[PDB]
Length: 37
DNA sequence: CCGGAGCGTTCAGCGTTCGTTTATCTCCCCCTGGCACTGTCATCTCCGTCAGACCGTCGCA
Image (cartoon, rainbow, N blue to C red; front, side, top):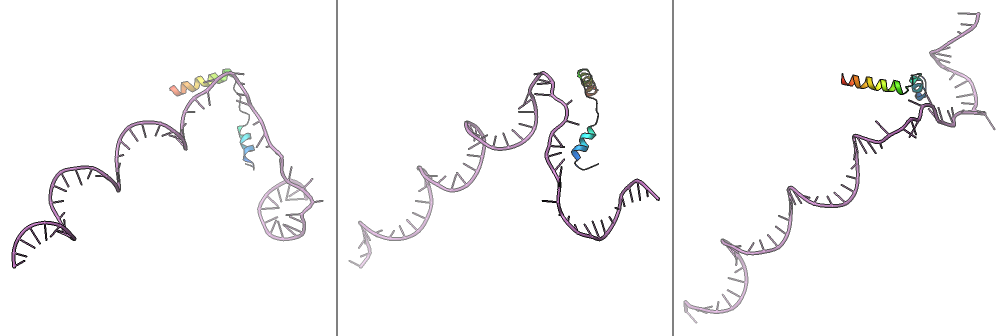
């Protein structure tokens, strides 16, 4: 919680794992499965 | 010596024309939705106030 909240938001994004092709299509399949459920 | 004709004014028959509306047809404005090689972290601030106080804050003692 500091000034210039855009920097705090960018740090809040943090080190999230980027998605390659296989992880992205697996997540899309899980998206469709959860939607169907 | 009234009588008639001509003239002034004032109204009832139907006959046309207005005053104000209505739905349909072009032209335009305005808002929500589509785009499928990939493309995954910016941005320059801020200095030669200034003058000292008021105040909380904070690590050292």
